[PDB]
Image (cartoon, coloured by chain):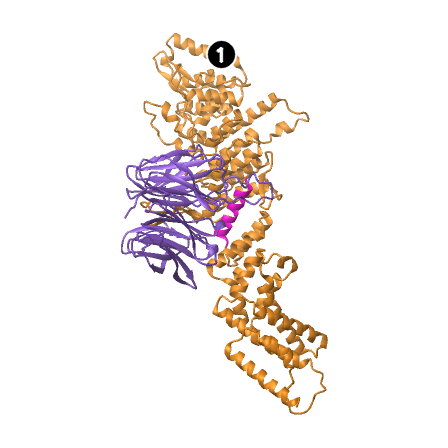
Chain colours: A orange, B purple
Amino acid sequence: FRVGWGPNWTLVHNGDKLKVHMEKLSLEQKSRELQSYLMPLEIELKNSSVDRSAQCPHFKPNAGVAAIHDYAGWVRNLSNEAGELEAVVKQWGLTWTLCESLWGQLKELEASLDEPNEYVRNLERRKAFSHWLAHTAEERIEEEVSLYGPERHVEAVFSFLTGGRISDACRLAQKSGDHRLSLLLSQMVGSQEMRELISLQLVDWNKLQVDHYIQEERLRVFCLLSGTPVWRSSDNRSINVCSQLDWKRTLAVHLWYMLPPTATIAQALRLYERAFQEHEEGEPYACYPLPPYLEDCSISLGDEPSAKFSSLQRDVCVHLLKLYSERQYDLCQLLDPSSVTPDPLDYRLSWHLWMVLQALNYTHLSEHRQGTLHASYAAQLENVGLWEWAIFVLLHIPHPHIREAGVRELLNRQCVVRESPESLAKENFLIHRLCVPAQWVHEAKAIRSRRDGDRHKEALYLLKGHQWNPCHKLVTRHLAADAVINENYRYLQSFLGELSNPEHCKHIQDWETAGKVYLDYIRVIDMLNLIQQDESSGCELEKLHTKVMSLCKWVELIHCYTAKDRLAQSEMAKRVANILRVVLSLQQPPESMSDSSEPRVPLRLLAPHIGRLPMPEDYALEELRGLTQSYLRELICDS
Amino acid sequence: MVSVINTVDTSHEDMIHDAQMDYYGIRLATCSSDRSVKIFDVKNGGQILIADLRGHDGPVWQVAWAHPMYGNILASCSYDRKVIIWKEENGTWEKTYEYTGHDSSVNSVCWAPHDFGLVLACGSSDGAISILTFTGDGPWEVKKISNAHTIGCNAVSWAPSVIPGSLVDQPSSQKPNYIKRFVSGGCDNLVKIWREEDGQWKEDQKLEAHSDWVRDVAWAPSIGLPTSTIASCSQDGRVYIWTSDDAATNCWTPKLLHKFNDVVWHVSWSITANILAVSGGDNKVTLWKESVDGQWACISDVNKGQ
């Protein structure tokens, strides 16, 4: 017994239930989930090229950014078309729209006829990333602003400022009667001098101990506008601007208020990373960038934080921002399912991200980890019943032998012998879209037909699979005797006729001693039936005679393994001897009509061939009695 | 979330030692201290007992399905020192072969990759490993590795037919170099890799990390990876993962996966080589998966509730 995984995540083990235990691991399947698999896979199939140079097709992602826009367009259409999106698809939306902001085509960079300077590219990328951050905060800011009401207008103003909506913050302040704050906010667009004046104002309030009479929420707005992340009031109160912000708004505040408008995305990320790391110069003031399924987990950071952050997975978006900033960033952490989903078996996003990163010319993922991503996502698709797409995932494996082995192994598990419209649609998808050799599908159907005991379908699929030697051995050992005994010659002729092609016969072991003998026997029956229906010319009778005489020699050489094979050999021998008599009687010129004797069969031509035929003892004795009586009659007519 | 899909009443009269699905996951073989092997058709949440195979004189320790290209063939091994080969013909199961060339309990059986033919490895408490080969013509051929393990061999597991990476580096015209290899575990605390060279079996590698009897060994299926992976478990409560990145270097690196508080009896790879099942003396089955950083995490502790 070997512990291992079977098809459709069936674990077979001898341990306690999570004696042989067979446990099926099912991801919870809601029937609405199948479209979440198919659309991303169709996007990748559109954005991939097929190399046909090898016996196993190889899929490669097309170089460029087209896949990123197709994915980002798909998630935008899904966000517009229905209520209650799976929380997972909302997270994929953040990831794909981030990839579009970082690497996608920008209309503003295409509007210039000249190659855009690296500075202009970095500026337009910073604007695209700034728009992404503002959009990610929109739903949450509208919720927060709805909760604060007219009485907490300063908190609602702060919420709009942390989404980059300075115009709406200004209008809210004005509507609430805070004209001084509204005037201040109107001046913040593009003046560094204004930031420095607010910083001086904060310092003067602290020196004069006037800051303790100011509302904390109001001081927090001034701290944000001054570009100071943490402020110490004269009362020794720490005002942290980032304390109520998610990691995305925290990073946005660093990009908009803490850094100059010329600062790169990589500078904003490094400043945010220092904000949640323990340093000798201050307490951490920013939240750690957790995945969204962990963002609401109140991980009480009890008194030892440095050893726990090395174990805490980061959001996939932070891994992508690191990869954009540092081209050699570790892809193993980025492509881990735990960066996206609570399920460690959900390889959906990780696999599609790897295809896009490969299209962007990232190649530093180890071959072992690539193999794990392809195998894990193919196994997920196999369990969902999309095994035809699991083949597509395996066709991306770089190594030809591993790719070929994995594809044939999946075909051998999942190929059905029963022709349903669904099975035929899947086969047509594999052969016509994936360019999988039809031979391998037929080989898998032959192996399955063998398991089911259907020797007919096994022979048919071995024939279609171009497996001539296995087909011939199966036909001769198991189909030929049953077809001869039941007189079903057309059925045996369909297989032996196709095998008789001069290109196939050269590859067949022992064709002349077995397969040809059965075919030549059928041809002799067919020619005799034709000669009985047409008043035939003597030339066809001589060709029949020469073939029958050859068959008498070869019927003896048929290897009999079963009692049925001996019965079929004896029936062939009896039939061939009767045919030889009929042919020898019909080869006579009509010039010996003396009325009253049966047709004179020439015994000298018949006797050497009847004595070599493997006949049953009773029939051989009847034939020898007939030959001796007719030989006695020849001797009585020649006297 | 792992969910129970089906519960099989095996109607065994004593302790079940092994339970193996066939290649298609439509048949379950089980074997027991009651000296029987039972075969069930398992479809759509039903089971039907289709065979009660009798021929062992003692507890049956392991069953192994052959590859379906050779038909419905099952091996069983027992305390009675026998290996029995069962075959289904025309819906009837029969004893097609019986091997009695071991002097003690045969603890493990494993079929070779189908690229090699009908080949079976058998590990015994006589300290030997027997390799049974059926060529299609005549009797089963037997190669016995005497003194494979001191005191006894507990487990055997075949390597994949194709070496990791051999499909990536082949320019379009050389056949894959098929190398017959298997791993064994024994009562000498060793994991050993065996290779066929010039028709003889040689100890290719000796893997030393366990401090007590190796109870089970499982060679991972090579689906498109450039690495060879083995799992082993022991009476010392440890599970090791052994990795080799280059089939030419013969270099094997142990990684401790976990230390349990009790004996670990069995290790079994998923067909996709991405999950390891581990069965302990604590009556638990734990599922382990490698993370993208190469770290092993427990993804399910299946409490036997009821």
Badge 1, how many Cα within 10 Å: few under 14, some, many 20+?
A: some
Name the image quarter holding residue B237. top left
Q: Is residue A406 magenta?
A: yes
Amino acid type for the residue under numbered disc 1: Glu
Name the image quarter holding residue B53. bottom left
Q: Is residue A210 magenta?
A: no
Q: What stretch of residues is rendered in magenta?
A: A399-415
Disc 1 secondary structure class: helix
Residue, disc 1: A196
Name the image quarter holding residue A177. top left
Q: Position of residue A95 (x, y in %)?
A: 50, 33
- What secondary structure is the magenta-colored segment mainly? helix
Q: Position of residue A283 (x, y in %)?
A: 38, 18
Front in this rendered view, residue A389 or B231: B231
* A254 over A59 or under it: above or below: above
Q: From this viewpoint, which residue is outermost toward the bottom? A: A595
Looking at the image, can residue A39 be seen? Answer: no
Looking at the image, can residue A334 be seen? Answer: yes
Q: Position of residue A137 (x, y in %)?
A: 47, 29
Does residue A595 appear left or right of residue A220 in this picture? right
Q: Chain of mark 1?
A: A
Q: From this viewpoint, which residue is outermost toward the top? A: A208
Front in this rendered view, residue A266 or B187: B187
